[PDB]
Each structure stands twice: as structure tokens, then as C-alpha cells.
Image (cartoon, rainbow, N blue to C red; front, side, top):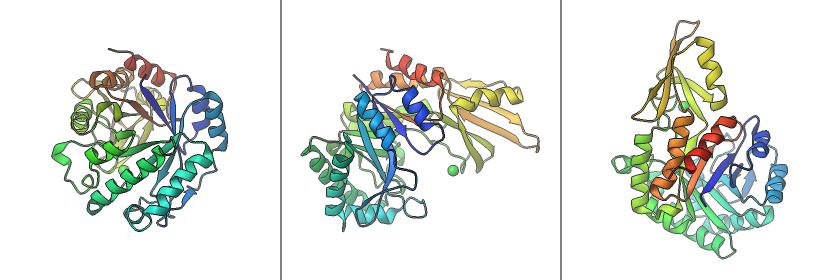
Length: 317
Ligand SMILES: [Cl-]
């Protein structure tokens, strides 16, 4: 009975995908909300997703309010995470609980990114208190965390996340096992299976596996050159291959698809993305590790073959 958590966020085609694929996922993170440094939950600038929430209630699909520490400029804010975890903790915890109640959410997904390394224990404590408060009301807690293994656990980007502590408090950790490479960096696998398995080994040693969700992207990246690239949605991969007549290579060691092409401006692009084999493989890791399930980022980027591959992999024993 694996959880199959879809992300409903600010992307074109989101609602069409939510409704088209509602037999494929069985929980949704409704990524429409921010929290302030005073602990108040707000909208994120996009229209309130009240239609999506109503749809999910009618389908009996659990919905989680996904709340981010994003400031008024649209930037991840270490300061907001610090404040919520310390001075505004009591307000934030109560407000998150009431927010879930008000919206008829089944729980909260805390998506706090750029947590400062100095806030490791503060953030763990916030999640402990929040988990107890949600549980006291029959609600659940999912915490989204960056994906890493021991070699990088002390990196400034990762040390704020104590998986052992977070996993003991939350119902699930949503391990963001994607963005292994990003446009700002050198080209490479975005969700390589070797890296993912290292990350999952690290997580399940520290957290009961049934409380872990892995993460599978419905996208890859297209680099013009290192540091210069853009997102390529799953649904657009085949058209791009066809536009340039590219011959894609399956990298078996990382279960990732790559290809190159020469653009009209003379640059040689490099794409790393997924195919059906790689998505099924990454979903099959739920059974290989005894995970609680998987998470897919995000609705609106995909087509029917993406969800067919997720289904196939989840059924692989
Ligand atoms: Cl980037």
C-alpha cells in the first residue's frame, strides 16, 4: 500500500494533470503556501487552489498543505526557517495545525529549504513539536529534505537536516532525490540511481524505511554549457530529440538518459533526463528498500507514459 505522492504546484497544466492522473497517485502535496517569520501561513502569490482541494476531497485522496519558507521576493529564506524554528515556533506550530484543519488537509508537508547549518537542532526541535501537535489532532507530517549520503552530510547545504531526528518525528520524509545536477552546475544525471541508492542507504539506516519516500523527477535539464541551462519537462523530451535528430544514450550505471545536439547559435547542448525504464527502476526502489512510497515532481510536466512507468516500477517485486 505504498504512498504515491504527487506535487501540485505552480506549473501550466497542473489541474489537467491532477484530474487526469488521479487513479495513479494516492496523496497530493498542495504546494501553494508560504510561512512568514512570525509563523503565519499565507498564499504564495498564486491563486488559492480551492478547486484542487475540493476535487481531492471528493476522490478521498489525502491532501497535504505544502508550506515553504519563501520570502516576499520569491527566495528561499534561512531567516524565516530560523525564526519559525525558534522565536515564532509556538505561533507557527499552532497556525500550521489550524491551517490543515481549516482546509481539510490530511496533514502538512513542511518544505523548508536552505535551512542554515547552525539551525540543525532548532529545525529538528520545530519538527518534533509540530509532529506531536499534528498527531494530537489526527493529522500527519511530511518533511521534504535534500537527498545526500554520509560523504556530504556535513556540507553547509545539508548539515541543517538531521534525518534521524526528523524521521523520528514525522510520518514521512520526502527525500528530494533529484537535482543531483542543476543548470547552475556541470551537466550530469539529475536523479542518478547510484546517487539515489547511496542517499536511500543513508536515510534508511537513520529512519524506518516505511517513513521514507524517494523522489522521481518528471523533468531533466538541458545545458547550453556548464552553468547555463534550463528545465526540460518529461512531456517535451521526445520532441526535442526529434527536432535535432539526436541519438540518446542510456547510461546504465546511473539509469539516466543523455543526449547532445548542436543548436543554431553554434553551442553544443547536453541533456540529462529520464525515460520509462529509469522511472520504473527508481519507483521499484520502494520495494527494494521497503520504503513508504514515492513522490513525483511535478504535475503538469508529464504525459501518460510517465505514470505508466511509475505504476510498472511500483509493481516490481
Ligand atoms: Cl539552477
